[PDB]
Image (cartoon, rainbow, N blue to C red):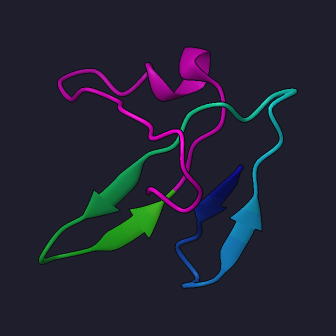
Amino acid sequence: LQCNTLDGGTEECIPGIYNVCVHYKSEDEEYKSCGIQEECEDAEGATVLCCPEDLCN
């Protein structure tokens, strides 16, 4: 699995840990970061959804 980075580059997400992905896009800022549902879920107020494909966030 692969995930997008805030630097604009691509990163490899291993299933052993990184199983989720989050993409934050705003008119004031834009960044991407995630890994484990346990950490991603920390984002209260919004829902975290990941795709079975590569580079979904």
The chief SS type of the magenta part is: loop
Compared to residue 53, the image places residue 47 above or below, namely above
**What is the residue that sits farthest to the top in this orientation?**
38
Residue 27 position, x and y percent, is: 12, 77
Side of 18 where 20 appears, left or right:
left
**What is the residue that sits farthest to the front in this orientation?**
53
Side of 55 where 25 appears, left or right:
left
Residue 39 position, x and y percent, is: 58, 24
Is 2 in front, or is 52?
A: 52
Residue 45 position, x and y percent, is: 18, 24
Side of 21 where 15 appears, left or right:
right
Is 37 in front, or is 16?
A: 16
- Report the residue at 67% width, 75% height from top: 10
Is residue 51 highlighted in magenta? Answer: yes
- Report the residue at 64% width, 83% height from top: 9
Compared to residue 57, the image places residue 8 above or below, namely below
Compared to residue 6, the image places residue 22 above or below, namely above
Side of 46 where 49 appears, left or right:
right
- Report the residue at 44% width, 19% height from top: 41
Name which quarter of the figure residue 36 lies in: top right
Q: In the image, which residues are magenta?
A: 33-57
Is 42 in front, or is 19?
A: 19
Locate the C terminus by quadrant: bottom left
**What is the residue that sits farthest to the left in this orientation?**
27
Is residue 52 highlighted in magenta? Answer: yes
- Report the residue at 36% width, 32% height from top: 49
Name which quarter of the figure residue 23 lies in: bottom left
Residue 17 position, x and y percent, is: 81, 28
How many numbered dots are placed on residues in this image? 0
